[PDB]
Image (spheres, helix red, strand yellow):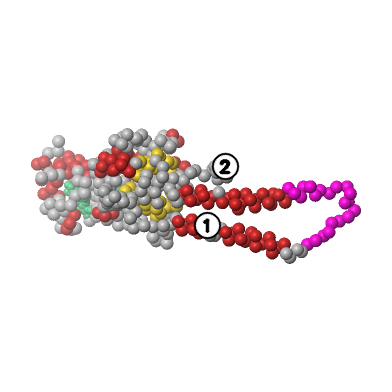
Amino acid sequence: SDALALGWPTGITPEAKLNRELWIGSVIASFAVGAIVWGLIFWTSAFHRKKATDTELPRQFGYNMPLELTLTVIPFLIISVLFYFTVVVQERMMHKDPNPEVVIDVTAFQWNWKFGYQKIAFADGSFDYDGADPERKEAMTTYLNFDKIETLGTSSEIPVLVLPAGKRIEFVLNSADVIHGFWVPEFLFKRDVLPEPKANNSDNVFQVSEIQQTGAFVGRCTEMCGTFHAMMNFEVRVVEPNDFKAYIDQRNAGKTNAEALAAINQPPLAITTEPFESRRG
Amino acid sequence: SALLRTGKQLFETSCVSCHGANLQGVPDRGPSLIGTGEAAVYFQVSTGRMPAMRGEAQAPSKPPHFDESQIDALGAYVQANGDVARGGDLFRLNCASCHNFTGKGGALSSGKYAPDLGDANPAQIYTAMLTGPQNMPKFSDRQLTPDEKRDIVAYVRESAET
Ligand code: HEC
Ligand code: HEC
Ligand SMILES: [Cu+2]
Ligand SMILES: [Cu+2]
């Protein structure tokens, strides 16, 4: 249940909840076989050299050709019942859909996670923002995705990303300088952001099917960036779908997350993480 | 304030040759101002056909095209209209793409250092960032708030002085 899964958080997407169902396939495979091998090494501690079989060397047997064939196929069929479930689950992931229902650029620059919003089309067909200006992009003579509802997140603001909690979400994963990493640990999933993903034969993007919980969760950076790699914390918020429509309408007129999250009566700063004292000074 | 009579006569003496509100050297860049302001029009464009006339540091010299009262007056005449932590993060997010390691995206030899910026000061940097030079697009209003512009200007200034 909770102890057999060695510390995984309960997934909030239905694709992450499939990992935690597969992670307790440690029981069927690892801790089962890992107790058989302990059950033979600690079984040969009742086989000491006692003072009766002292002038008699043992049977001196070296080749048992039925045993290296039975105990080869049995480790082979366990990794043949794997490479089935770990192909089905990664095919449940890596999945795309031409109605993504919100598209969020993440644009991991050097050390503080500049987010941003692109086109969004709910299943009701009611919101339909669709904002990503190409005229700002033509000021750079690139691969980055610029837009107008971006969340900057300076060194003391600790960027809070807001996304609804019943809809499909797409994360276009870009980076300005170095390969960083994008890891909300509650999304039991992680993809490294690259400088130029379409030039590196990368896939650049992933999608979650929905979110099944409300609240607000931590996000960290994983692949190493440099000095302040431990300071790149972002913090998603899974607001209601009705509070998300009131988030952008306060934000489209132009405010900040200290003011846009206040109009939907939610704590404006990050509540599961906070800026570091070792970096601000 | 800046004397607009001095500003008109300075425009006629030194800028009418390439600019009649137009530009004869790069046609579209004459009535085209991005994030136009008195501070930006005052700041010497670091790239393009003509470099800023001001002598290095704003010191008196024998080849200055102008003195300070003349600059302010002309910048005003053209302008008729009729936290270092934040600074470092803003630099990395918006300017590192072309100015990584204090360098220049257009030319490797060209740099953001004071020798490259001559008579640089915080105000001159802030102004080019606001509306910007020919090489980099304007940042004020469009991309960065005043605190962010102020912080990034300070960070660039401290990095170049040290
Ligand atoms: C996509 C292009 C581009 C971006 C983005 C850009 N710049 Fe520039 N910058 C230039 C070019 C080109 C020059 C050379 C001056 C010219 O264009 O004549 C320049 C020159 C400068 C200079 C003067 C250096 C000198 O010696 O003359 C400063 C100061 C400067 N930039 C600051 C910034 C700051 C601060 C940012 C972001 C926070 C930034 N730039 C982003 C293209 C860019
Ligand atoms: C009183 C103000 C003023 C006078 C006089 C002036 N300029 Fe400029 N110049 C500017 C400003 C401000 C810019 C920055 C571009 C902008 O306005 O967007 C600039 C930019 C330039 C650039 C492009 C540099 C770059 O990197 O983008 C060239 C070339 C130039 N000027 C040439 C000249 C020449 C040649 C003269 C006179 C023979 C001249 N200028 C007189 C204000 C002036
Ligand atoms: Cu990172
Ligand atoms: Cu990192």
Out of A196 and A248, give the one closest to the viewer: A248
| Crowdedness near tag 2: few (<14), some (14–19) or many (≥20) residues, C-alpha within 10 Å | few
Q: Which mark is residue A243?
A: none
Residue A32, percent from left and from top = 63, 51
- Give the main secondary structure, helix, strand or loop, of the magenta stretch: loop
Q: Quadrant of the C terminus of chain A?
A: top left
Q: Which residue is mark 1?
A: A85
User: What residue is drawn where x is 53% and y is 51%?
Assistant: A22
Is A59 contained in the magenta span? Answer: yes
A137 inside magenta stretch: no
Asked whether residue A250 is in view, the answer is yes
**Which amino acid, mark 1?**
Phe
State the image quarter where residue A186 is shown. top left
Chain for mark 1? A
Residue at screen point 32% across, 48% down = A117
Q: Nearer the viewer, residue A246 or B90?
A: A246
Magenta-colored span: A42-62
Secondary structure state at the residue bearing disc 1: helix
Residue A58 coordinates in the image, percent (x, y): 84, 56
Q: Which residue is mark 2?
A: A3
